[PDB]
Amino acid sequence: LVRPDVPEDQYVDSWYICTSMTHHMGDYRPWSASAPPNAFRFRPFNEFDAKGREYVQY
Amino acid sequence: MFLIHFVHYKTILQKYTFKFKHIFLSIDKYNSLFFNISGILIWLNIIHINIILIKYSFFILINNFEYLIILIST
Image 1 (cartoon, rainbow over the protein chains, first blue to last red):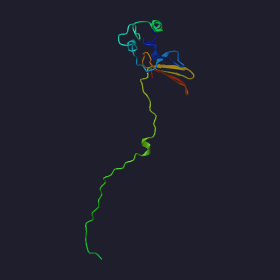
Image 2: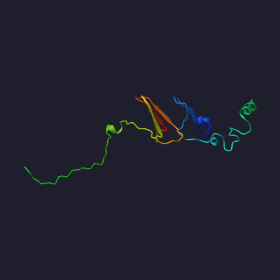
Image 3: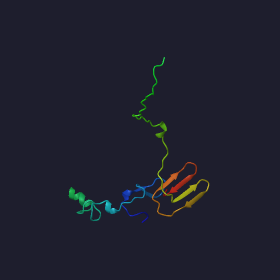
Image 4: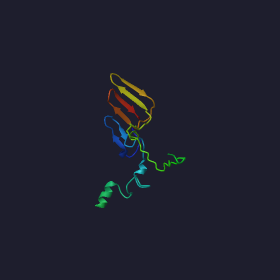
C-alpha cells in the first residue's frame, strides 16, 4: 500500500502532482460503509458477483 | 403681560426604537480555511525544503505567483 486501503471513489488523481488525494480532506470511510450491513465480500447483494447479477437479471 | 408661573411638562418617551446598521457591517473580508502546515517547498533560483512534521499528507497546495511554493498537508 501507498495510500490507505479504502474504496477508490474517495481518491482523486491530482492535477500537477503525481499522487492521489482524498476528495474530502483527510476523512476516511472504511469498506464496510460502501456496502449494506454485513454484506458478503462487500457487495450490493450477496447472491452473486457483478456478472452473475447481470445475467441472472437478463 | 404675565398672569402665571408654571412648571414645564414634556413627554420625552422614547417608546419606539429605530437602529439602522451602518454600511461597513456588511463589507467583505477575506476568510480562509486553516489547517496545520506539515511542510513547505520553495523554489525560485534554488530549491529549499522545510519539513515541520512528517506524516502521510492528506492535502497539497501549489501556488505559482512569485516563487513556486508547495504547501504540504497545509
